Image (cartoon, rainbow over all chains, first blue to last red; front, side, top):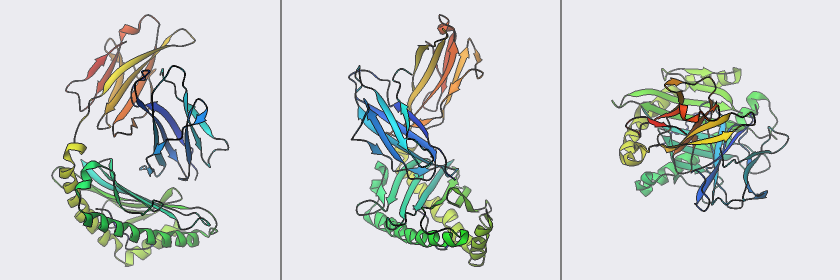
Length: 9
Length: 99
Length: 273
């Protein structure tokens, strides 16, 4: 299972 | 940053005339990811070429594998041609079936 | 050691629609899944036989995650232009790599969560999985945002948690494909050079996994002095190939030995011309 972005740069 | 692609051309098996084979064009170490790859037979573009749709390396440079099915004859010649923004001219690497 | 890694890319193309977004996932170093936003009906798709076993909720779940990630990278590309004061007409790339290395004892060895903008390091999660390394000043802003937001702890929970556990699952369900070995088939080619001497090239074809040793010997002593080489390179079918060459005097070829060491061989391969 892949990773999920939860924070923006 | 613009990194210049390294291009390698090689067959899956030792070439024998009449024996179906796969020819590969392995393009590494380039950036930006936009790139154009052709495989040529007898100076003309091969229509049925497939890509591996690309990925990148530990060091962030991009790489992709092109390949096409072919049967070696005694007179055919093959090359891989790459257009990329880091080069003023397309780059051609000829396949040497005797290496 | 084994690994589960995800390679992600977003590339902008002003005037040609939304940025191209791509995801590829690997076990050890074998591709098994991919998402491409320029596909027809973009979905997370299997790229290896053994992952097709997963049910429809797996692919619906991963497609949701990818589409969520694509939206975030759209914002990040727009933000990146502000941090670096770049015009909005150029193409820019953002890259992401995340995953886990684990040993047989199931223990996490290393966790990765790192980014690059236009091909250069931006921010990376450190080995402690608690601090961030920020390349330039622009990435320090991001580091401050992620510090006060507890980003490291949420992301670490994927690295120590879901990443390790699905790798175990993938390693059992794909065992016959991932931990197989394929032996090298070797041969030697002979080419007279214009100076009269002879290039001998030792090929090794169709081996898996990728690691291999290819050396030339002269009645017993290795020849790393005049040995040309290519890096191991992939075939379409998931196997690899390599060659090493030396220059030898004509008529003395049978004095040189090529040695191949690989997992798929019980003992090294010796061969000569």
